[PDB]
Amino acid sequence: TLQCTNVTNNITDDMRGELKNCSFNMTTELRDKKQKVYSLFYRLDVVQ
Amino acid sequence: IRSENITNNAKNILVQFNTPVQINCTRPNNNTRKSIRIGPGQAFYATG
Amino acid sequence: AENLWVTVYYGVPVWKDAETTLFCASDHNVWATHACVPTDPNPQEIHLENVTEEFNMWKNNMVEQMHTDIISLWDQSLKPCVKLTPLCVTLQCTNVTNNITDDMRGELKNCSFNMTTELRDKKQKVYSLFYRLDVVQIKEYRLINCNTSACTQACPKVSFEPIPIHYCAPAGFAILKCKDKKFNGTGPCPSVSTVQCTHGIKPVVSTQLLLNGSLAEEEVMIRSENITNNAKNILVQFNTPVQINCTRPNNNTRKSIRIGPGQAFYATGDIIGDIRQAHCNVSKATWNETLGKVVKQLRKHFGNNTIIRFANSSGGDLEVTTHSFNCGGEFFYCNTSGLFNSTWISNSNDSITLPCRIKQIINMWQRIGQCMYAPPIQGVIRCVSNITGLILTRDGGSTNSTTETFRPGGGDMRDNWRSELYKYKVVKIEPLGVAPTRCKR
Ligand SMILES: *[C@@H]1O[C@H](CO)[C@@H](O[C@@H]2O[C@H](CO)[C@@H](O[C@@H]3O[C@H](CO)[C@@H](O)[C@H](O[C@H]4O[C@H](CO)[C@@H](O)[C@H](O)[C@@H]4O[C@H]4O[C@H](CO)[C@@H](O)[C@H](O)[C@@H]4O)[C@@H]3O)[C@H](O)[C@H]2NC(C)=O)[C@H](O)[C@H]1NC(C)=O
Ligand SMILES: *[C@@H]1O[C@H](CO)[C@@H](O[C@@H]2O[C@H](CO)[C@@H](O)[C@H](O)[C@H]2NC(C)=O)[C@H](O)[C@H]1NC(C)=O
Ligand SMILES: *[C@@H]1O[C@H](CO)[C@@H](O[C@@H]2O[C@H](CO)[C@@H](O)[C@H](O)[C@H]2NC(C)=O)[C@H](O)[C@H]1NC(C)=O
Ligand SMILES: *[C@@H]1O[C@H](CO)[C@@H](O[C@@H]2O[C@H](CO)[C@@H](O)[C@H](O)[C@H]2NC(C)=O)[C@H](O)[C@H]1NC(C)=O
Ligand SMILES: *[C@@H]1O[C@H](CO)[C@@H](O[C@@H]2O[C@H](CO)[C@@H](O)[C@H](O)[C@H]2NC(C)=O)[C@H](O)[C@H]1NC(C)=O
Ligand SMILES: *[C@@H]1O[C@H](CO)[C@@H](O[C@@H]2O[C@H](CO)[C@@H](O)[C@H](O)[C@H]2NC(C)=O)[C@H](O)[C@H]1NC(C)=O
Ligand SMILES: *[C@@H]1O[C@H](CO)[C@@H](O[C@@H]2O[C@H](CO)[C@@H](O)[C@H](O)[C@H]2NC(C)=O)[C@H](O)[C@H]1NC(C)=O
Ligand SMILES: *[C@@H]1O[C@H](CO)[C@@H](O[C@@H]2O[C@H](CO)[C@@H](O)[C@H](O)[C@H]2NC(C)=O)[C@H](O)[C@H]1NC(C)=O
Ligand SMILES: *[C@@H]1O[C@H](CO)[C@@H](O[C@@H]2O[C@H](CO)[C@@H](O)[C@H](O)[C@H]2NC(C)=O)[C@H](O)[C@H]1NC(C)=O
Ligand SMILES: *[C@@H]1O[C@H](CO)[C@@H](O[C@@H]2O[C@H](CO)[C@@H](O)[C@H](O)[C@H]2NC(C)=O)[C@H](O)[C@H]1NC(C)=O
Ligand SMILES: *[C@@H]1O[C@H](CO)[C@@H](O[C@@H]2O[C@H](CO)[C@@H](O)[C@H](O)[C@H]2NC(C)=O)[C@H](O)[C@H]1NC(C)=O
Ligand SMILES: *[C@@H]1O[C@H](CO)[C@@H](O[C@@H]2O[C@H](CO)[C@@H](O)[C@H](O)[C@H]2NC(C)=O)[C@H](O)[C@H]1NC(C)=O
Ligand SMILES: *[C@@H]1O[C@H](CO)[C@@H](O[C@@H]2O[C@H](CO)[C@@H](O)[C@H](O)[C@H]2NC(C)=O)[C@H](O)[C@H]1NC(C)=O
Ligand SMILES: *[C@@H]1O[C@H](CO)[C@@H](O)[C@H](O)[C@H]1NC(C)=O
Ligand SMILES: *[C@@H]1O[C@H](CO)[C@@H](O)[C@H](O)[C@H]1NC(C)=O
Ligand SMILES: *[C@@H]1O[C@H](CO)[C@@H](O)[C@H](O)[C@H]1NC(C)=O
Ligand SMILES: *[C@@H]1O[C@H](CO)[C@@H](O)[C@H](O)[C@H]1NC(C)=O
Ligand SMILES: *[C@@H]1O[C@H](CO)[C@@H](O)[C@H](O)[C@H]1NC(C)=O
Ligand SMILES: *[C@@H]1O[C@H](CO)[C@@H](O)[C@H](O)[C@H]1NC(C)=O
Ligand SMILES: *[C@@H]1O[C@H](CO)[C@@H](O)[C@H](O)[C@H]1NC(C)=O
Image (cartoon, rainbow over all chains, first blue to last red; front, side, top):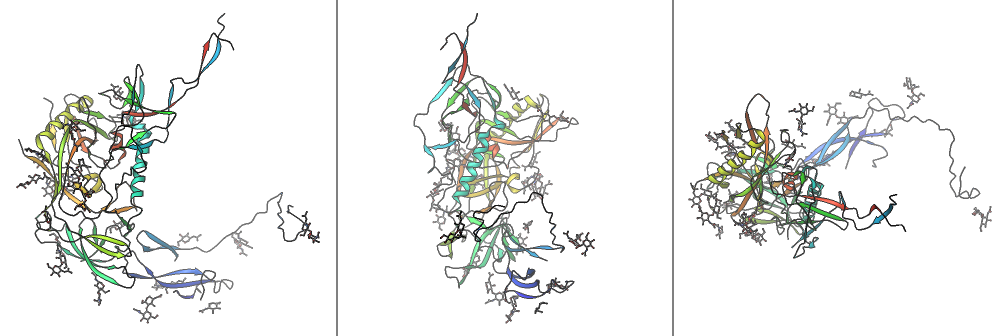
């Protein structure tokens, strides 16, 4: 599950909603640990 | 102009130019890549 | 006046230096002989009169192919084996201090951890004894390999003991063998034969000391690609072997932990009795007079009044700075500082004890990201081997000084394979020939 917000810092009118700032929990090298990370995804790559 | 059956509109027409047309394609964003260790020897490359 | 015409001869005895793929012959084990042709009970050697052949052990492609074959056999013997991905967890480790000697302090860690079971929704608290060399602190530890790659446990039924392997040329190729004793591997061999397969060569993996190999029949043989280049390894072959006795004396207990459906991880349970260091013994007098032989043969290359000194390995990985080898499933890394510690000036029953450290996480060939976990061996382990040679490296050697210093080397197993294939080469037969003769068709 991705928790996504809108990327709105220095975007043009034709880039609105095109990039998602998504934070998620991810596995680590140790099987018993999780890391909260984030990534920029494209609107075409994620579905609500 | 090359078509398997030019009178069949279900056949694709292949056009070959004698002179090329120059196309200049850019992604202008200065993208930052970060690397996330998701397992032993396993990296996922996120957009920072 | 001559009246000579072209004449074609088929079946001529002519050959060229060639590179081809040799095949395996032999009389559960890593060095899979279930894909090797049976060896002929009476192999045929054809002694070629008057044939003087060019040999070069340092460009022998047989060595490269054999290295590839050994690596591939190692890789495919590990494929149907447990991948220890679950083992990359947090370990809660304490010191093993019950009946340890002063030289085993901190060497063993008693590590408890949570592990998966055969049921996906259940965890088991288990513990294991790990070696100081295998764990790194994050009281909390992790296995050394967990930030590089997951490790494959060696299947406990597969044996690591080397089996002799014979290398045979295909149709249209011949293996030429140099029968010349005193041969130093490069140049013209005037005593040549043809063999369909090489002799049984055991894939003995070791560093700084060649074990269980072939001996020189006349005297100690020094072989270097360019003896005056100190960046080239010197291969020493003994005429008489040196007996080395290596033991891990701990009475190890192996327990089996079900980490998944049909998946077992073999942990070290508890050492029954006293905990004390693994080691190797070499006869002091035998080693001393063997080094005397090596020195007498090195003076032939480095001067007759020079000082010949033997010193420790310079540095690097634990694989290269120690005599690293495999003794009945366990992986030893022995400190050969009591062996190479002496100077030689031109003019009883005790033994040298080399302390050894055990490892379970193994990177055999000089590769990164592909590691093997050695399961613990039940009980005490002891082996006896022949040192039949050395891999040395000369130190510096500018014209400033008259002392030559040699240090144990190794790491690259191609030098181990080159010490057995030095007297072999592969050629391809060129049967067609054209000559002048008086006939006309
Ligand atoms: C140089 O050559 C010498 C001589 O050839 C080598 O020394 C010999 O090495 C072999 C192998 O290490 C050794 O054979 C072992 O002897 C033990 C004592 O008799 C045996 O216990 C052992 O058998 C066990 O292991 C085999 C696989 O290795 C299994 O097939 C076998 O079933 C046994 O396994 C059972 O028992 C163990 C322990 O409880 C358990 O883990 C298993 O699951 C299973 O229950 C071998 O037969 C010779 O004894 C050595 N000989 C001498 C004189 O030392 C030397 O190693 C070579 N050097 C190098 C560097 O290669
Ligand atoms: C995407 O979201 C993350 C998290 O909200 C942003 O990272 C934060 O950036 C601020 C400064 O801008 C820092 O003070 C925070 O500490 C950061 N948080 C983390 C978890 O790193 C990031 O800037 C956002 N990126 C975009 C393009 O919107
Ligand atoms: C990462 O995981 C944590 C915990 O697993 C999430 O935090 C929990 O969020 C739920 C709501 O869905 C709450 O009910 C819990 O109380 C939270 N627990 C903690 C410890 O905070 C967190 O939301 C996850 N983050 C992302 C980006 O998915
Ligand atoms: C090119 O494609 C057309 C369309 O499929 C072919 O002509 C049709 O053939 C069907 C066959 O039953 C007739 O019912 C149609 O009346 C035809 N239409 C026309 C416009 O001719 C035509 O035969 C194809 N050409 C070739 C060379 O195969
Ligand atoms: C595509 O064309 C546009 C103009 O229509 C280019 O935008 C110009 O880029 C140059 C970069 O050297 C700037 O100096 C101009 O100020 C830009 N003008 C405008 C109106 O944006 C764009 O760079 C071109 N892209 C490619 C890949 O050729
Ligand atoms: C390693 O640690 C384990 C756990 O601390 C030890 O196992 C315990 O041994 C005592 C007797 O010495 C028993 O009473 C406990 O029930 C055992 N605990 C478990 C979880 O089995 C083990 O003896 C230690 N081994 C070494 C070599 O230190
Ligand atoms: C095995 O897992 C259990 C539970 O997942 C661990 O016990 C927890 O330890 C944390 C500290 O890291 C405490 O905050 C929790 O309250 C503990 N929970 C319980 C139920 O005891 C335990 O430490 C793990 N064991 C090992 C060896 O890693
Ligand atoms: C260590 O070296 C000795 C001496 O070369 C080996 O003993 C010889 O074994 C061969 C078997 O191929 C016999 O034909 C010789 O007669 C033996 N010679 C002596 C003096 O015993 C011994 O087998 C070697 N040990 C190992 C483990 O390689
Ligand atoms: C053995 O290797 C050495 C490399 O050190 C070769 O000699 C050197 O060649 C370079 C080439 O420019 C010179 O700069 C060095 O001065 C040479 N070394 C010495 C000590 O003179 C040498 O030719 C090689 N031997 C053979 C037979 O190939
Ligand atoms: C290596 O040599 C040492 C001696 O320095 C051996 O230790 C002896 O082992 C025997 C076993 O039969 C005992 O009876 C002696 O009391 C031990 N003496 C000492 C001083 O430790 C050791 O066993 C040898 N190991 C091998 C593998 O040969
Ligand atoms: C290595 O072990 C062998 C035995 O496995 C030792 O050979 C013994 O040597 C003594 C001489 O001190 C003889 O009395 C015994 O009869 C030999 N035993 C056998 C079975 O041959 C050898 O001495 C050991 N070498 C070292 C350096 O420890
Ligand atoms: C070869 O011998 C030297 C000295 O005889 C060893 O150097 C020692 O290294 C350890 C490791 O940190 C130090 O604690 C000692 O203080 C060093 N001794 C001296 C006298 O400086 C060297 O380690 C040996 N070579 C190998 C490969 O072990
Ligand atoms: C290999 O053995 C030598 C000889 O014992 C080690 O050198 C000793 O190192 C200790 C430090 O732990 C010093 O206290 C001794 O004085 C050193 N002795 C000599 C003769 O130099 C050497 O450290 C060992 N190699 C490794 C890698 O541990
Ligand atoms: C993100 O932006 C798009 C377009 O500006 C908008 O339709 C969408 O509702 C926004 N989502 C948010 C603010 O969560
Ligand atoms: C992109 O950003 C990096 C880091 O700030 C900078 O060094 C680089 O010059 C930038 N590239 C462009 C084309 O602006
Ligand atoms: C384990 O023993 C070593 C050497 O005796 C010591 O340096 C280390 O601190 C010990 N660790 C413990 C008691 O956790
Ligand atoms: C793994 O960890 C060790 C020690 O913590 C470190 O030396 C090594 O560089 C690390 N490897 C990678 C790939 O990060
Ligand atoms: C020993 O090796 C050297 C390497 O240059 C070679 O020239 C010499 O011929 C070899 N020895 C004999 C007897 O051929
Ligand atoms: C090792 O321990 C087992 C079980 O305690 C015992 O039967 C065996 O004899 C021991 N072996 C040695 C060499 O002490
Ligand atoms: C090396 O030899 C010297 C004698 O000059 C001795 O004092 C020293 O202990 C030896 N080192 C080892 C590791 O045996």
